[PDB]
Image: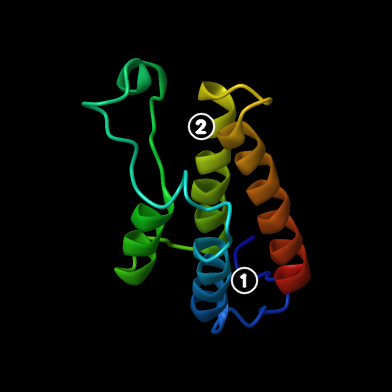
Amino acid sequence: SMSVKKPKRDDSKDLALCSMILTEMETHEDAWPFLLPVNLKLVPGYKKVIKKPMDFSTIREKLSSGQYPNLETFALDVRLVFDNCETFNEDDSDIGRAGHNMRKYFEKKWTDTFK
């Protein structure tokens, strides 16, 4: 509350560390469904159904331009990429399996770096 604070966590490396995680996600062999925005002219149903599209290139641009206020807003966009994927793709599909694999990969890096 006013004039009553928990000890200050060092957040000075968060930006660099989120960049490194995002590099590791970009270079994973199962990243290909997530590298670029879904083409809303060419994929029937995507525009109407997926209310907030997100992809790795869009996260990279937000990261590089100071549009994440903290590491939680960064994690929310990464998770949005996988939540969107589950919404649109059957579990038993190449893209459906890609999304589950990448979400696991991300969550372990996130816990190891920050928890």
With respect to residue 107, does 48 lie above or below? above
Q: Residues within 10 Å of mark 1 (few under 14, many from 20)?
A: few
Q: Position of residue 91 (x, y in %)?
A: 67, 26
The image quadrant that residue 79 belongs to is top right
With respect to residue 62, does 47 lie above or below? above
Q: Nearer the viewer, residue 4 or 108?
A: 108
Q: Nearer the viewer, residue 95 or 50?
A: 95
Q: Residue at x 68, y 25 (%)?
A: 92
Taking 19 as reference, is 8 left or right? right
Mark positioned earlier in the residue sequence (2 or 1):
1
Please state, as top left, top right, bottom left or bottom right, where the C terminus lies in the image. Answer: bottom right
Could you tell me the amino acid type at mark 2?
Asn
Q: Position of residue 96 (x, y in %)?
A: 61, 32
Could you tell me the amino acid type at mark 1?
Ser
Q: Position of residue 52 (x, y in %)?
A: 39, 32
Question: Which residue of the protein is positioned furthest toward the left in this rendering?
Answer: 41
Residue 3: numbered disc: 1
Residue identifier under label 2: 84
SS label for mark 1: loop
Q: Residue at x 76, y 60 (%)?
A: 108
Taking 11 as reference, is 50 left or right? left
Q: Position of residue 44 (x, y in %)?
A: 32, 17
